[PDB]
Amino acid sequence: LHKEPATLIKAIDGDTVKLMYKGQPMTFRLLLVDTPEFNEKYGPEASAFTKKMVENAKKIEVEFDKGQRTDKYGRGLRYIYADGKMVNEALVRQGLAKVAYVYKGNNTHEQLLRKAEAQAKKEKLNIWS
Ligand SMILES: Cc1cn([C@H]2C[C@@H](OP(=O)(O)O)[C@@H](COP(=O)(O)O)O2)c(=O)[nH]c1=O
Ligand SMILES: [Ca+2]
């Protein structure tokens, strides 16, 4: 798995962001994770967490998996990194996302994220009440 460069265009919500990628604007969906919609409980907090993370970052990078790169709504499916810290893992670790939409074979990172969710659940963080 290899990382490519990308520039923040706009934060959107907990698990989507708009990025300039190979010269084109694109909406990106985070792999393996599901935040609440903004209208749901911990939605605003998820959006807020991802916004700060991508906005405060000097370098954002994107990482596709072995399977689907672009989902049926035209969104780039990626692990996203903010100064080398994975947003996907980070949300799960804070209990602001659930591990979700794990399809084979697009799940290189499942074990690391489930590792993070175990710890967040143990900790009763945010969505784990
Ligand atoms: C995360 C992810 C979502 N999706 C699609 C499944 C979709 O469900 P539907 O067919 O129910 O729309 C949608 C859900 O994402 P959102 O959580 O952004 O709505 O995104 C993928 O196809 N692959 C993925 O890896
Ligand atoms: Ca969602």
Image (tube, rainbow, N blue to C red):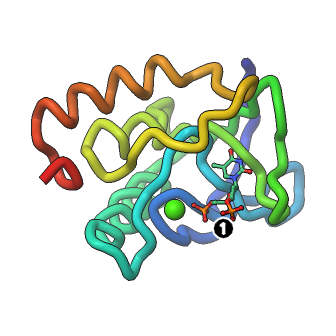
Quarter of the image for the N terminus: give it: top right
Q: Dot 1, crowdedness within 10 Å: few (<14), some or many (≥20)?
A: some
Mark 1, residue position: 9
Residue at (26% x, 26% y) in the render: 118
Tell me where residue 12 sits by quadrant. bottom right
Q: Where is residue 54 shown, x and y percent of the image?
A: 49, 54
The residue sitting at 77% across, 51% down in the picture is 76
Is residue 41 shown left or right of residue 16? left
Q: 121 or 3: which is nearer to us?
A: 121
Residue drawn where x is 39% and y is 45% of the image: 98
Q: Residue furthest bottom?
A: 39
Instruction: Pinpoint residue 31: horizontal percent, then vertical percent.
Output: 61, 41
Q: Is residue 98 above or below residue 85?
A: below
Q: Nearer the viewer, residue 37 or 88?
A: 37
Question: Where does ligand 1 appear, by image quarter?
Answer: bottom right
* Residue 26 picture location, percent across and down: 79, 63
Residue 83 to residue 108: above or below = below
Q: Is mark 1 within 8 Å of ligand 1?
A: no
Residue 56 placement, left or right of 93: right
Relative horizontal placement of residue 127, taking residue 110 as reference (left or right) = left
Quarter of the view holding residue 4: top right
Residue 100 point in image, percent of width and height:
51, 43
Residue at the extreme right? 23
Q: Element type at marker 1? A: strand
Q: How many marks?
A: 1
Q: Amino acid at mark 1?
A: Ile
Residue displayed at 60% across by 43% down:
101
